[PDB]
Image 1: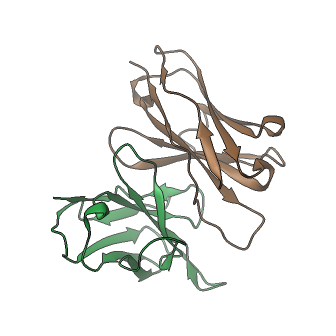
Image 2: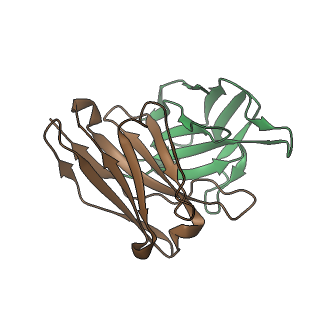
Image 3: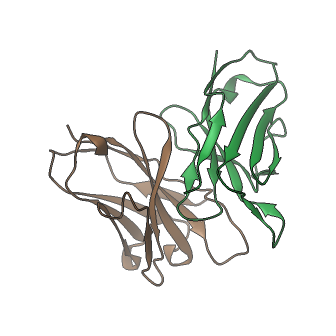
Length: 120
Length: 112
């Protein structure tokens, strides 16, 4: 089947940076859009941004754009979520999802297991 | 931009019982070009990743049971389940899949 393998949990000190990985299995990301969603203990989900591994174009949420950086390495079929200067507010679970662009319509079906990031 | 509002937030249910959830969008999600509404529903159990239940506000994902019915148009949508089961106790989110940025509702948690 298709699968989105995510890296392990993280515990960083306020001010440090962090890189999260979302490796794809069963499909080449060069044909899917890699999105990133953040979820705090609250419950509500929040879109952070996406990227096009093919062209390298990105798309962030205005509130995240100045903190998150989504990178992609086709050579390794991996997408990254770089978070800078962490604060308590950054403590959450970060999932990675995909969307096939080469098709009429396709929702955000497959998702990664989500990697927890605790700062405090 | 597009605000997703779901209600009620919490809902005590009993097995076999029918349940109705509502999700209202800030602006219309109906694409006049294909008459399809870009709204999708999710299910989330604790310690588990979000799962796709329905997209285009009413089309069931390959796999989900019929007891999951989504409907509504443009601004108002609702989720329904005829005779809720036990493994139906998660949180359900509706999501605007029309335009950027993608927005999710706060969700409705089904309780014991």
